[PDB]
Image (cartoon, rainbow, N blue to C red; front, side, top):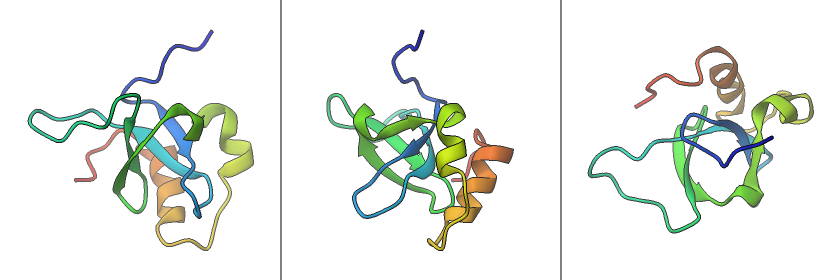
Length: 93
């Protein structure tokens, strides 16, 4: 059975106006800004941007990649695809 989302989890994350996007639940580093309650900091592969998102927007990677892991015109997306597949846990600082 599924647990709650934990930092390190790979997802497609859905933002308004963007397609399901390859991402990861990040850790909060010491002294860095904390997300609102019931939000997770999401690092988006390719764009390397952070938003805060609840679970309704978070699609587990393993299960969703057949639907969503296909290339896309969008800036950063294909880079995004490569990162999540090939090195999802690197520092892209």
